[PDB]
Image: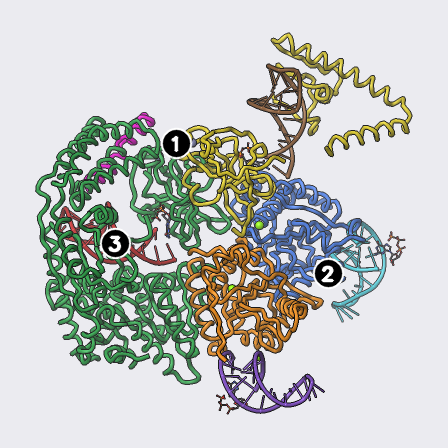
Chain colours: A green, B yellow, C orange, D blue, E cyan, F brown, G red, H purple
RNA sequence: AAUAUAAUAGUGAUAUUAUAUUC
RNA sequence: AAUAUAAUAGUGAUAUUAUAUUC
RNA sequence: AAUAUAAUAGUGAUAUUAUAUUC
RNA sequence: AAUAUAAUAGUGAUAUUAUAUUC
């Protein structure tokens, strides 16, 4: 191995036993820094003593990568490397696994949970901690929970030995600071969270660092919105006719905006609490209102999609929607709405088949891609968009475009509800830096709004000299946001370089002050009468709160053979094992093919049981009759009977 | 009020009144039903609007007479001769008893008998312990719904958990059950709920039982 | 991933629980064969039970490679993969390390020494054993020592449950045999050393294999 | 349909705790036993199975319990058998124990078979139920079995041990002249059965007193 | 043949008897 | 999934439904 | 179920949606 | 320190060397 000088320079404060936040550009090879710090830390101990290192990776790919590298590197030195992730965390002696290994790679939630249970009594068992992407240490994030434990031990009278804390990040961030001084405050608070007395940056060796990681040139493309909407002109008529149908049953803002989305969601939640003496009629009209607001929401989504993409993509979005609706079953209301939609279908497809209507944004994007690939046919591009719908949209737009034929698109999204041939990779977003992918000498941000940290991190894809990053937007605000983010970066670097000049002792004192203050701030009746849980769509009786049991102070299940008649089920599209639970199938409302999503069906220990979310139900008090809606089970306040296997 | 009881069954409370409402049965069940009338003075009414039913059970009474008379005849025979005749009949029956169609390997299509939706392929169908038929692949899982079984039972090595129905446009036709078999959680389907379309030919045929359906039946292997 | 048919064919005798010597050309992807057999072995157990697989690599590079691949493969399925080599073997609770992990990669000398020391009381702790380059099982080689323990337990009076044994080799070897009968005897003795009742080779799928591993033309320059 | 106090008495046992169940005669301890056994057998995962042994000290109680358990657990797929002095001889006791989930025994059978060696350890059972457990003391067969249990526990055998459930209407204070000595005797009895819990009816007492009434006692001198 | 309980004698281990059970 | 019985069409093997049972 | 980020509404604790992650 | 392979000398057990590996 042959480490670069700036890596030794960055690792030097940590090797001196100083708690250190290491701030260096993305792709500078921080992994080697970690290896150096750990190697020195482990080899520094005398014979009668030994060190224990814990590395925190926030995402599974980084987890496996780091575990592999550390194992391959430190096996020859006589240090056992292991790891505990969510998959392997259950039914294993975590305490022994920690005790029997020198280097342990961990996702932070494991440590938070094991500290909370008490299986790992103290953080004193580790002599060194390393936080990957340490800028995440703040608020309620698992990192910050770990550090809550740490600081609770430090500031307390336990007087147990504490591990050296080493953070790693490309950007510490200035937060919401409007000026350099406030930025200094934020950074100091972050250093207090990680108990770090030193911020390590490349200074002496900068000339070496700049020959490795290069800063890509950033261009701002400000375009115009499409001049005339025929599509929105006619679909506003379907929104109007749908809210007119809603205007029949009600007894009681712009289209294509987030304001309308908020409004229609609040309306949808308002329709669920309406009540009548006749309950079946109530179910009919509530199902009706739910369906109307749903179609309204989908239409709105179509408007937005076509604002940011082709009108064909919005049309196909609606067509996919109604395809699914047809798959659901025949409902009078759904059949009606689909009918009125199908009446306007000819006119619609007439209006997106025209070449005249192509949006200025896609034209400009096409121009960018054309020019850049004309100059360099070997160009690898990465295209960031806000939503997955837009991912599919541009995916189809590229190969549906004859001029873009040189492009070989690919898809990168999340899992949940050069030498290869992919020239361009369309993606939503990637948490922090992540695993290094192929170097993109072209980065296109399409209506992208990030923070300063994500801005600095996205440069890691542009490490090569001559990389370029375009920001294409019709909003004209986005430009300003990115600019003030650049200014935020300036504030950050300046404040850091100012902090580095302070005497370390004084800084430790300020840090201790902040920590104690934050600890002071941090240290600062359930209803017993039965409630009913009704479907949010068809208002059908699902459960009684007397039948609800709480597993592990988190998940909620139902007891009795009565509930088994209220739901149907189909195998889960994305089977996943969370905690001690194993997902098997999805459960839906069984009454008259309502099919509203109630929750999941899981295997827990020996039991096969349903788990429901309060978000999908309406809570009716038997005594008062008052119906209420609830965020999550945390905000629903009633006495929750623990799940008892012997019951 | 009851439907029927196989043979004598467990001994019930004595009924001095037994009423047969449009009831038709054999001689054996006739003689067995008397067991509920053991006490003196018990009565049995046969109530029907059919001039036939009465006739049925009186020819049954005649059958009983024939039975008793025949037994009384057999009891007069010499045991050796009876053994000989019995042996003769046994050998005959064994001779008659001691006295397979070529399977089709063409891939068929199992369609829902109700909505004609494609459910399964005969390449996906695997047979467990010569009797029960399952469907492999994740393709099938999107074709069916499931409801918790109203009467869960354990038969042989299988445990019933849910009933499975058609998923398309709320067809909800009964395709079979969903069971726990050894380590595996797997669906079991009945051929009587499906129509077989060989789309090489395009011909649709109906089978009531699996053993009357002759195609290539591959054994279920845990090693697949 | 997408396994080639001859790999499934080679793994099939092992997935049926038979102790099996797998004999296939070098570079046919035996790694994925091991992954297949191991995955099937671990997933076959009911809920209340679990298996323990031990992989024997004779060399440190092979040790690290296999440990890495197995770790990256089986972490998602909820199986802990670890290893013990000469560097990490000292002053560690080897028994606990074996106990607390589902898949364990060892250099054979660790198991030999720890069996002799008594820290590992029996091979009954493993439900499966895989020998890389299993032709090395003979004479005083560590593999053969391990198998001496195995066979002493098997042929001994009190015998607990024994692990399935899978060997992996490109060539079993004929020894010094001058004819097919002596060769047959050598191969049978090797199978006896590994307690293997089956020798798995590629037969049905030969064309596919010959499209992957080609036999180089050999010239002799005198 | 069980009475509430029966569930209350069964609850500590169903939680896996070694328990001495103390309730008045006639409260229906049989159903308590049935509940404990049922929950104990059903709690095991697929790859494992439990084995329950029920000690009845007298042949009538032996036959009664055997009949009741056989009739009750046949449905759930648990084979119930028994061994008394009549059928104890010239039979493979080890196989009979191995091949059945619930085994009803008179204590002498298990003592004899333990010291003979046919049953190597009590680890073969996942649950033990002593009927009239107050009899566990001195040289009584119950106490001999428990001597095997404790010899295994306090030793370095490191084998798994069965959950122990006693059943009695009275534990007894022995010769105790005061509450302290009584406490000591009861503690020693708990030690004998390795029980950390004594289950009595508390919440449901009013229901229990509608079932078993206390008769009036007169003294004629 | 073993075990339990009660009475009695003995400082006690125990001993006698009565009663019951088990193998 | 198998088995038995009854009614019903067929000369019959069978077939449909009903009823019951077993694995 | 928890967490983070972004936009939107609100003076704010927050709320909605979007995106991503973890257990 | 142990193990394997190859060549060699010897009828063989082995022995020398070469080579590789492991603890
Ligand atoms: O020493 C005793 C013993 O060896 C033998 N004996 C008599 N009954 C039993 C028994 O129930 N169990 C065992 N193991 N051994 C037994 O008889 C010897 C003495 O004879 P007894 O006269 O005392 O016994 P008997 O049957 O004549 O009288 P009883 O015991 O019924 O009252
Ligand atoms: O083909 C049948 C069969 O394989 C299986 N099956 C259902 N019940 C049993 C049984 O009692 N014994 C055996 N050996 N096999 C059984 O199910 C397949 C058909 O499913 P069904 O829908 O007909 O079964 P279901 O439970 O839904 O109805 P029912 O027979 O109990 O009344
Ligand atoms: O209330 C939730 C929760 O109890 C449970 N649940 C589902 N996924 C998880 C998980 O990853 N981690 C934890 N701790 N708990 C989980 O399901 C209830 C809600 O059901 P959902 O319909 O939201 O779950 P579903 O799988 O359908 O959607 P998603 O998990 O993919 O987002
Ligand atoms: O007798 C040997 C032995 O006791 C000891 N020794 C040296 N290396 C090892 C080893 O790798 N493993 C074991 N078990 N024992 C070892 O040294 C004695 C002989 O010393 P050498 O001069 O022959 O060894 P050296 O390190 O000088 O050279 P080398 O081992 O590379 O050949
Ligand atoms: Mg191979
Ligand atoms: Mg298992
Ligand atoms: Mg060796
Ligand atoms: Mg079980
Ligand atoms: Zn509903
Ligand atoms: Zn259908």
**Is A605 on the left or on the right of A357, as rendered?**
right
Tell me how far mark 2 sits from mark 3, CA to CA. 77 Å
**Is A79 on the left or on the right of D153, as rendered?**
left
The residue to which callout 2 is attached is D114
Chain letter of the residue carrying label 3: A
The residue to which callout 3 is attached is A408
Tell whether label 1 touches label 2 (CB within 8 Å): no
The residue to which callout 1 is attached is B170
Tell whether label 3 touches label 2 (CB within 8 Å): no
Chain letter of the residue carrying label 1: B
- Same chain assignment for discs 2 and 3: no
Q: In the image, is residue B79 part of the stretch drawn in magenta?
A: no
Q: Is mark 2 within 8 Å of ligand 1?
A: no
Q: Does the residue labelled 1 lie within 8 Å of ligand 10?
A: no
Structural crowding at the residue carrying mark 2, measured as other residues with C-alpha within 10 Å and reported as few (<14), some (14–19) or many (≥20) = some
Q: Is residue A263 above or below residue A280?
A: below
Residue C49 versus residue C186: which sits nearer the camera? C186
The region drawn magenta spans A262-289
Q: Give the mark count.
A: 3
Residue at disc 2, secondary structure: helix
Residue A278 versus residue A368: which sits nearer the camera? A368
């Amino acid at each position: 191995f042959k480490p670069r000088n700036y890596q030794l320079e960055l690792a030097l404060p940590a090797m001196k036993g100083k708690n250190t936040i290491i701030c260096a550009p993305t792709g500078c090879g921080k992994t080697f820094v970690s290896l150096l710090i750990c190697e020195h830390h482990l080899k520094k101990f005398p014979q009668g003593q030994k060190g224990k290192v814990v590395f925190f990776a926030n995402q599974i790919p980084v987890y496996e990568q780091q575990k592999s590298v550390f194992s391959k590197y430190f096996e020859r030195h006589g240090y056992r490397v292991t790891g505990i992730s969510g998959a392997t965390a259950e039914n294993v002696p975590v305490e022994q696994i920690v005790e029997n290994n020198d280097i342990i790679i961990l996702t932070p939630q494991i440590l938070v949970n094991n500290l909370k249970k008490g299986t790992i009594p103290s953080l004193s068992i580790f002599t060194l901690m390393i936080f990957d992407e340490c800028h995440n240490t703040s608020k309620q994030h698992p990192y910050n929970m770990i550090m809550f434990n740490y600081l609770d031990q430090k500031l307390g009278g336990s007087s147990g030995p504490l591990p050296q804390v080493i953070g790693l990040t490309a950007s510490v961030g200035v937060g919401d600071a409007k000026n350099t001084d406030e930025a200094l405050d934020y950074i100091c608070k972050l250093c207090a969270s990680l108990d770090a007395s030193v911020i390590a940056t490349v200074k002496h060796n900068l000339e070496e660092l700049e020959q490795v990681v290069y800063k890509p040139q950033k261009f701002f493309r400000k375009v115009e919105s499409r001049i005339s909407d025929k599509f929105k002109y006619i679909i506003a008529q379907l929104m109007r006719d749908t809210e007119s149908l809603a205007k029949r049953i009600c007894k009681d803002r712009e289209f294509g905006t987030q304001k309308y989305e908020q409004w229609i969601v609040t309306v949808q939640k308002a329709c669920m609490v309406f009540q009548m003496p006749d309950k079946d009629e109530e179910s009919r009209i509530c199902k009706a209102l739910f369906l109307y607001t749903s179609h309204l929401r989908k239409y709105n989504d179509a408007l937005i999609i076509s604002e940011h993409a082709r009108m064909k993509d919005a049309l196909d979005y609606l067509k996919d929607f109604f395809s699914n609706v047809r798959a659901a079953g025949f409902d009078e209301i759904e059949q009606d709405l689909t009918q009125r939609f199908e009446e306007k279908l000819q006119e619609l497809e007439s209006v997106s088949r025209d070449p005249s209507n192509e949006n200025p944004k896609l034209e400009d994007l096409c121009f960018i891609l054309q020019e850049e690939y004309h100059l360099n046919p070997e160009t690898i591009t990465i295209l960031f968009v806000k939503t997955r719908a837009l991912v599919d949209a541009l995916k189809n737009w590229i190969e549906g475009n004859p001029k873009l034929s040189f492009l070989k698109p690919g898809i990168l999204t999340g899992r949940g509800k050069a030498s290869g041939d992919h020239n361009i990779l369309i993606a939503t977003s990637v948490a922090d830096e992540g695993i290094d992918i192929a170097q993109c000498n072209l980065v296109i941000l399409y209506e992208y709004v990030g923070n300063v940290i994500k801005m600095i991190q996205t440069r890691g894809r542009g490490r090569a000299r001559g990389s370029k990053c375009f920001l294409l937007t019709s909003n004209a605000g986005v430009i300003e946001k990115e600019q003030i983010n650049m200014y935020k970066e300036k504030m950050m670097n300046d404040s850091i370089l100012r902090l580095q000049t302070w005497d370390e002792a004084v800084f430790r004192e300020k840090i201790l002050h902040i920590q104690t203050h934050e600890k002071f701030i941090r240290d600062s009746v359930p209803d017993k009468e039965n409630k009913k849980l009704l479907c949010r769509k068809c208002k059908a009786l699902a459960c009684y709160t007397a039948d609800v049991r709480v597993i592990e102070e988190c998940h909620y299940t139902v007891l009795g053979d009565a509930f088994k008649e209220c739901f149907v089920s189909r195998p889960h599209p994305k089977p996943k094992q969370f905690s001690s639970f194993e997902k098997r199938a999805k459960i839906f409302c069984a009454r008259q093919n309502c099919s509203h999503d109630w929750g999941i069906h899981v295997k827990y220990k020996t039991f096969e049981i349903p788990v429901i979310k309060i978000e999908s139900f309406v809570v009716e008090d038997i005594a008062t009759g008052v119906q209420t809606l609830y965020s999550k089970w945390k905000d629903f306040h009633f006495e929750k009977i623990p799940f008892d296997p012997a019951e | 009020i009851a439907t029927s009881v196989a043979d004598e069954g467990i001994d019930i409370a004595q009924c001095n009144l037994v009423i047969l409402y449009e009831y038709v049965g054999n001689v054996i069940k006739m003689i067995q039903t008397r067991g509920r009338g053991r006490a003196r003075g018990s009565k049995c009414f046969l109530l029907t609007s059919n001039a036939g039913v009465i006739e049925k059970e009186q020819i049954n009474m005649y059958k009983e007479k024939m039975m008793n008379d025949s037994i009384l005849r057999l009891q007069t025979w010499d045991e050796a001769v009876f053994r000989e005749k019995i042996l003769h009949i046994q050998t005959h029956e064994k001779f008659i008893r001691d006295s397979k169609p070529v399977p089709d390997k063409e891939n068929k299509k199992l369609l829902c008998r109700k909505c004609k939706a494609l459910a399964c392929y005969t390449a996906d169908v695997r047979v467990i312990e010569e009797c029960h038929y399952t469907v492999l692949g994740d393709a099938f899982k999107e074709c069916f719904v499931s409801r918790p079984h109203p009467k869960p039972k354990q038969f042989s090595s299988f445990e019933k958990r849910a009933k499975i129905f058609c998923a398309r446009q709320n067809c909800s036709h009964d395709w079979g059950i969903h069971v726990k078999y050894k380590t595996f959680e797997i669906p079991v389907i009945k051929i009587e709920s499906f129509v077989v379309e060989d789309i090489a030919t395009g011909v649709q045929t109906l089978y009531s039982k699996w053993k009357d359906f002759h195609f290539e039946k591959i054994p279920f292997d845990p090693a697949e």
